[PDB]
C-alpha cells in the first residue's frame, strides 16, 4: 500500500482521463497550480514547464510531520505528462533527511532503505518508526496528486 515500488525504487504514480479536453488545456491548468505552488519557493523548489513536450517537472524539499514528536525532511521529484484527454503523474527519487533527536543533525536515507515492503523492510536500525515514514509519505504524495487532479478539472 504505502510504498509502491517499480524498477527497484519507491515510485507513486497515477494516470487520469479528462474527457474531451485538449493537451493544451490540461497542461495550462496543471502548470498554473505548479507555478503557484512551487515557483516562488526559490531556495527549496524548482519547476520546469516544457510547453514543447507538455511536461512539468518539479523538485522539492519540505518538512514532513511523522507523529506528534517526530518529523523528517522529505525530498522528491515529480513529473507530469499531458496528452489529449489524459495525463500521467509520477513521484520518485524520494529521500529523507532525518535526525531522530529532531535537532537538525540530518543524515540522508534513500526511501528504498527505509520504507520498502511498507516499512517492514527498513534497513536503518536508527529509524524506530519506519511505518510512520511510509504512511506520511503516501498521504503527502497522494494528496499532491489530488491537488493536481483538482487543478486539471479546471481545464475545459
Image (cartoon, rainbow, N blue to C red):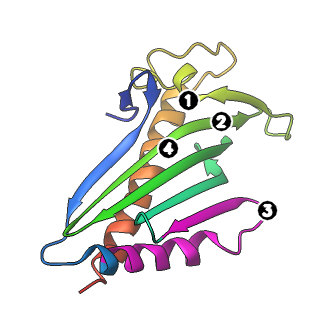
Q: SS for tag 2?
A: strand
* Residue at image mark 4: 136
Query: Badges 2 and 1: C-beta atoms under 8 Å apart?
Result: yes
Residue drawn at x 38%, y 28% is 5
Vertical relation: 55 (above or below) 28: above
- The residues bearing labels 4 and 2 have C-alpha atoms spaced at a distance of 12 Å
Locate residue 133: give its quadrant. top right
- Mark 3 vs mark 4: give the one in front: 3
Mark 4, residues whose alpha carbon is within 10 Å: few (<14), some, or many (≥20)? some
User: Could you tell me how far apart the alpha carbons at marks 4 and 1 are, in whole angstroms?
Assistant: 12 Å
Q: Residue furthest front?
A: 52
Per the model, the C-alpha gap separating discs 1 and 3 is: 23 Å
Of callouts 4 and 2, which one flags the residue occurring earlier in the amino acid sequence?
Answer: 2
Asked if the residues shown at circle 4 and circle 1 are in contact, with their CB atoms under 8 angstroms apart, the answer is no
Give the residue number, with chain letter if any, for mark 2.
96
The residue indicated by pointer 3 is 43
Residue drawn at 31 percent across, 81 percent down: 25
Alpha carbon distance from label 2 to label 1: 7 Å
Q: What span is colored magenta in the figure?
A: 26-50
Q: Give the number of the disc on residue 111.
A: 1
Q: Is residue 37 magenta?
A: yes
Select label 1 or label 3 by which is in front.
3
Q: Earlier in the sequence, mark 4 or mark 1?
A: 1
Amino acid at each position: 500500500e504505502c510504498a509502491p515500488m517499480k524498477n527497484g525504487k519507491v515510485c507513486y504514480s497515477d494516470d487520469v482521463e479528462i474527457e474531451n479536453t485538449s493537451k493544451l488545456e490540461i497542461f495550462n491548468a496543471i502548470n498554473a497550480w505548479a507555478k503557484k505552488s512551487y515557483g516562488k519557493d526559490v531556495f527549496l523548489s524548482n519547476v520546469n514547464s516544457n510547453k514543447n513536450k507538455g511536461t512539468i517537472f518539479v523538485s522539492s524539499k519540505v518538512e514532513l510531520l511523522l507523529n506528534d514528536t517526530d518529523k523528517t525532511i522529505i525530498k522528491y521529484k515529480m513529473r507530469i505528462t499531458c496528452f489529449d484527454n489524459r495525463y500521467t503523474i509520477e513521484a520518485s527519487d524520494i529521500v529523507y533527511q532525518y535526525d531522530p533527536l529532531n535537532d537538525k543533525k540530518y543524515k540522508t536515507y534513500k526511501a528504498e532503505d527505509v520504507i520498502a515492503n511498507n516499512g517492514d523492510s527498513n534497513t536503518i536500525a536508527l529509524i524506530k518508526d519506519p511505518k510512520l515514514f511510509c504512511n506520511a509519505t503516501f498521504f503527502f504524495v497522494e494528496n499532491l496528486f489530488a491537488d493536481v487532479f483538482d487543478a486539471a478539472q479546471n481545464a475545459e
